[PDB]
Amino acid sequence: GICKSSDCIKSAARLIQNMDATAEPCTDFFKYACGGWLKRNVIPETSSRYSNFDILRDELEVILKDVLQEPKTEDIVAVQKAKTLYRSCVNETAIDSRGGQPLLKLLPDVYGWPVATQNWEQTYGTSWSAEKSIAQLNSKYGKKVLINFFVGTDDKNSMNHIIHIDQPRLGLPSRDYYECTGIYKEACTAYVDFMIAVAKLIRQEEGLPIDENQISVEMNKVMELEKEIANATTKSEDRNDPMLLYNKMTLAQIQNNFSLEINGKPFSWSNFTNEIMSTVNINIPNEEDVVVYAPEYLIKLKPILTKYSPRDLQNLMSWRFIMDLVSSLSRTYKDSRNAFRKALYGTTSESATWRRCANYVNGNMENAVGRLYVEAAFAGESKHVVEDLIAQIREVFIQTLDDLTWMDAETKKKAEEKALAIKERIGYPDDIVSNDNKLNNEYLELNYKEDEYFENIIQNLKFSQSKQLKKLREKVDKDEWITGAAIVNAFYSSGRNQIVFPAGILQPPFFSAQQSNSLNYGGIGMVIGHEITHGFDDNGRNFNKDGDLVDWWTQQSANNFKEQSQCMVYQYGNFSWDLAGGQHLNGINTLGENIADNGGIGQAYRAYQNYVKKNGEEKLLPGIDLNHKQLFFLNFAQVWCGTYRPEYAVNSIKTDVHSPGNFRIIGSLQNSVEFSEAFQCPKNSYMNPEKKCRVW
Ligand SMILES: *[C@@H]1O[C@H](CO)[C@@H](O[C@@H]2O[C@H](CO)[C@@H](O)[C@H](O)[C@H]2NC(C)=O)[C@H](O)[C@H]1NC(C)=O
Ligand SMILES: *[C@@H]1O[C@H](CO)[C@@H](O[C@@H]2O[C@H](CO)[C@@H](O)[C@H](O)[C@H]2NC(C)=O)[C@H](O)[C@H]1NC(C)=O
Ligand SMILES: *[C@@H]1O[C@H](CO)[C@@H](O)[C@H](O)[C@H]1NC(C)=O
Ligand SMILES: *[C@@H]1O[C@H](CO)[C@@H](O)[C@H](O)[C@H]1NC(C)=O
Ligand SMILES: [Zn+2]
């Protein structure tokens, strides 16, 4: 009773090579399941993180390279455009020969970069305003500085679009970095040195004199200013309650509450918002309803911006613009980022050009590339099997509601109701393959040049912003996918109440027809449960079956949810990460993903048990002395095998909403009674604490 096919052989070998059978499963299942993986898969010099997910993503890029690099005579226009874009990207000779000219020619559009201008006040100072400067960077390039403005879905009205105002992100990964001490020290130094080096490059190419000391003065002022702004932002821990974040008010009320003085003049919110929306010819009146996510931040901004000159402010705003473009220029400009990249990611060099280009084209033409990918690599027969798994796990969630004693009867009915309303998306949208006309029409306005990569990416930035801004008076398109198909990931959307599984994740170790059911349920099964559970985590539970931010919880059940979930806040917050120098996980910011992990694996296992009950036992795998209950948890863990560079471990522990794979494995299995039964773990072994957390 042992499988002998070539498929079972490499499946078994993969499992065997990744595990470390010398480790005790009940002491550390990560070391047990991924010990061999760690020795076998050294982090590539161009990778900041390496893992099962990252490996699959690298392998997907190879496929994209194959289907993008060679023109074919029968290529429809949409595909021709994708290949032209790719070709422009990988021609490094053409890029190198242009130096920094594409950026230098463009810089006036954002009111220049004062430190690298001959006479900034003379040339730009006369027509400059913060309203117009922030607006141009926003509406043309999607670069959000000082104040974030975006058109998105209305939290409380999921069919409508509405303007949002929020605090912006920073040049460094998080607000914590701006302490610039200890583990943040090198990053801050490299960040300012990065500014200075680029200022020198641009001035040299412009034929301007180089004053080393003067540049240093201006760029340290940039850092001084961004430090204050960072300190003014609200912590991520205080932004996980969607109900508290939602503040609807009129533009008039915004002007009233959030006045700002810049260069001695009052900031006009009407001017700012209309400088943005006029790009798509939409007027914004004072009665316009607006959603403000960060009122505290805007108030704290008041005494900060008065202290700085237009040169100071523009030096920061244009630097935020320039820092993300320098790697799209010649080698000299690429290399200016070296020390900065290493400080944040630990990587010694940028990844291969063709890899970046494949990813870039995928990111900007997800339907055209999704089409090429699925035709080359995706078995459509997979869809119906995944459909059935989703049905099983959805039903398991609903049945589990009876077991949960911390919910009253009517909250259970509402929860079941939302679970039933969840819509699924699997593989790819059929239209990208079956309807050439629609696909071509999507990219009608795009026209790329073979030898102008930088011009192409500028065109893409404008197009992307214009497309989103135009939605303000339009209803939300229900059928629109929230991801490309050539993606190794899965998603839950609160606003649409839907779960999405693109073709890219429907492969080993997650899922295969040539893979054991134990592995399939432990893999994509757990992921399906994960996404479903997201509809009921600390964020998702606030949205109803139609995607609206409304309270459908009784006071008692809501209180009980918070009590049950608090256990997981403490559990993961107590985890210390050696790769991050002993820093602790953020239990609050990772709560949602941890709730989904813990709920999902339990749902998946129960669904698997039900399957075995009705269909019988499976054939054992050769060379592996484990039953299929144990293979379920082994495959679950190997889905999350991986490691981090120290610099990026520090980065991710402050920015990633997920726990590191290491602790997703330890955390979820510590809370799993079924895991400890499968591996016969003694009570109070590290993997089997007698106190366990439970939400779903
Ligand atoms: C971060 O911002 C807070 C205010 O948002 C600053 O706290 C103020 O500090 C000054 C000077 O120490 C005091 O006079 C105020 O009373 C403080 N206000 C509050 C509300 O605490 C804080 O100093 C800033 N930190 C940094 C590093 O810039
Ligand atoms: C915008 O400003 C108004 C006016 O101060 C705020 O409304 C006041 O809120 C306080 C309590 O926070 C009440 O005591 C006042 O009666 C309210 N006044 C008015 C005219 O409504 C409002 O809360 C502010 N908005 C935000 C998001 O801070
Ligand atoms: C890259 O660009 C250079 C300069 O325009 C050109 O000579 C060369 O043929 C291009 N390479 C390809 C593969 O088209
Ligand atoms: C913003 O104000 C400037 C000067 O007051 C004006 O020229 C410009 O037209 C205004 N923008 C909009 C969108 O009205
Ligand atoms: Zn998730």
Image (spheres, grey):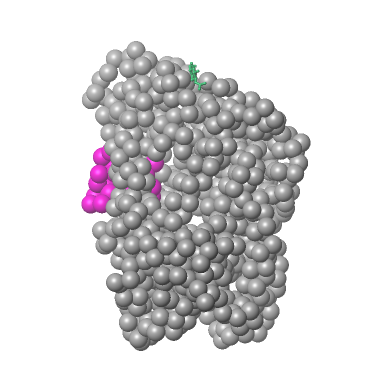
**Is 369 or 114 nearer to us in this picture?**
369
Q: Give residue 492's position: percent from left, percent from top.
A: 59, 60
Q: Give residue 462's position: percent from left, percent from top.
A: 59, 31
Instruction: Name the side, left or right, on which 521 lies relative to 649.
Output: right
**Is 473 or 302 nearer to us in this picture?**
473
**Is 507 or 436 nearer to us in this picture?**
507
The outermost residue toward the top is 207
For the point 68% across and 38% down, which residue is it? 470
For the point 40% across and 61% down, which residue is it? 641
Q: Give residue 190's position: percent from left, percent from top.
A: 28, 38
Instruction: Name the side, left or right, on which 79 lies relative to 639.
Output: right
Split into 4 quadrants, where in the image is the C terminus? bottom right
For the point 31% across and 45% down, which residue is it? 346
Name the image quarter holding residue 36.
Answer: bottom left
**Is 209 or 540 nearer to us in this picture?**
540
Does residue 416 sit above or below 286 in this rendering?
A: below
Whether residue 599 is visible, yes or no, is: no
Does residue 485 sit above or below 322 in this rendering?
A: below
The stretch drawn in magenta includes residue 695: no
Does residue 12 sit above or below 111 in this rendering?
A: below
Name the image quarter holding residue 409.
Answer: bottom right
Q: Give residue 298's position: percent from left, percent from top.
A: 48, 48
How many marks can you see?
A: 0
Is most of the magenta stretch helix, strand or loop? Answer: helix
What stretch of residues is rendered in magenta? 171-191
The stretch drawn in magenta includes residue 176: yes
For the point 65% across and 33% down, which residue is it? 79
Whether residue 634 is visible, yes or no, is: yes
